[PDB]
Image 1: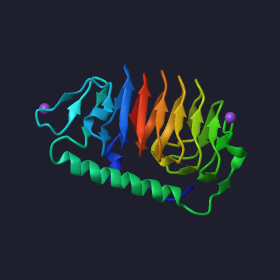
Image 2: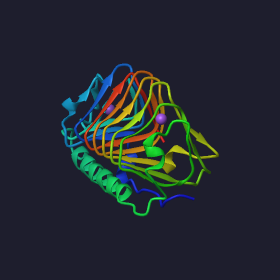
Image 3: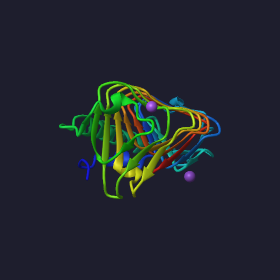
Amino acid sequence: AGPTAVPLGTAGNYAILASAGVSTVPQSVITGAVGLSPAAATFLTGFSLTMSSTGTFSTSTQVTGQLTAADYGTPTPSILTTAIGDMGTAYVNAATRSGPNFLEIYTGALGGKILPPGLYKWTSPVGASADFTIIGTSTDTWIFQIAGTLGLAAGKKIILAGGAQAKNIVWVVAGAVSIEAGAKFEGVILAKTAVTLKTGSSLNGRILSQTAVALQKATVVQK
Ligand code: NA
Ligand code: NA
């Protein structure tokens, strides 16, 4: 049940892919690669980076995986350009799916709700001030199209039930995404604009932003 999968292309090689910057307030934890393009590596802030001897990637104690930026050595710039283009195609694939199953459901207030598989569209801000549950099997899919901001309140969690898995959940969000302190987020975020995770928050999925990503003492695990 649910919509056809969203193709990520080579954007599916990253835990975090951004265009304008990736910042951390240490200590954050990222499991998976971090890519940044077309911004230069100066816009990776807070990672205390060490360049590979190759000059094509860098490492941080905060990241399990490689970091890459647009001014690193060949072929990193070209690999990232392809990834950024794939992210752009993924955003448009998800954002332009037609015929939502659910339109303006709950006027965007998701706390306490149970969300079965489907294509959802909101033309408003969306948020949750309480936990909410995404329920379906391990093969079901969800696409959440959000024209406004997306917010998850402090301490609140997106709970997967039934077998639902993070790689089959896509949030395609035009406005800024805020994940408050101690919150737990699930799914792939295709963000047109910025994304922030606050202290002690976590995300299982990916953060694919066309602007900047801020990680304040936060955890991101690729799914
Ligand atoms: Na090396
Ligand atoms: Na709510």
